[PDB]
Image (cartoon, rainbow, N blue to C red; front, side, top):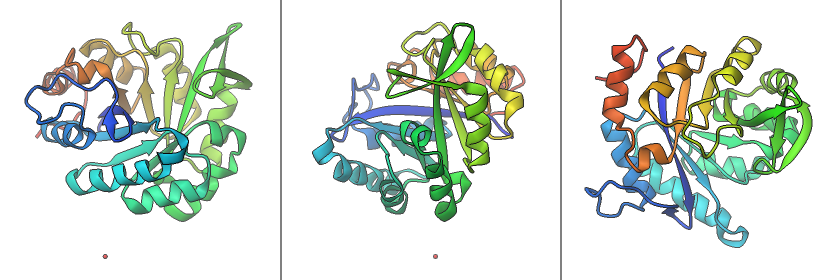
Length: 251
């Protein structure tokens, strides 16, 4: 019931892609050190998205999650090309709390159920990329390249039905901008599901996070706005608490 702030990190070959501005770190491109620091200054969860080339990817992702699990005591999610149960399983067993799936879920919705059977619904995060097409919200796969022709309304309901634990709602209309979260999209989805909704795409200033929670998001995920310190994590949580948002401060 508390709202969560989630730092998302894009990684490749064990490096934070495009790095970060925290000059206090020994290595500002080290995902484990950056992730650890984030947990120490108030981030509620981490999210890692891997884009390593296929031949080294499996091993690279497993090394990342094991290293992260050692140094971090907050929940974390891993994703990026997770296409089947076996891949999801190895990553959870090696240390991840949750996996994030999108394209493979749309093409085989029972993948949601198979992962949840073994690891519980809470281990399954479905990322839904959506955008407006002829006045309707539609689901997009393959990093936004493909219009599936599936209505957002229908996919959300199916996703909960198949046993997902959380939904990340990413607005292609906002990704790569700093104009704010897609609050209209979040409000559209909120009454359709009982699952936690994680907002993603468009974060630019602290007020955007307040707007997102008002819209009904249970968590807010953000990338470079945090890494380049356009927003400060502690200021953000102080700001949100100040304006009525239930965030956590202090075998």
